[PDB]
Image (cartoon, rainbow, N blue to C red; front, side, top):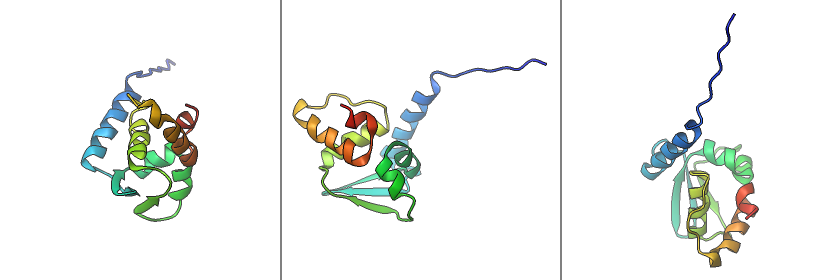
Length: 113
């Protein structure tokens, strides 16, 4: 007779922090993204969910992907967003580059800054 519903407002945040902690260790990371002279380990499921570019890319098999036209430190910030919902203390002189990286990768919130 009785139907029960409940919503955990803390969940999606805790989950993202845990996913970011994993990423720091490379745990469960199933792709490496090479950007200039840097390699970033990440999770395909998260990248696919959050980037229209990666969503397209990860329909093809492959464990290493290479990005052109984005500087490593800018990609580092895009990934920090993907793994947190936030951009934190970005120099204003980098913002145009960050926006452009969001545009290229199809990360809507970043492209809209």
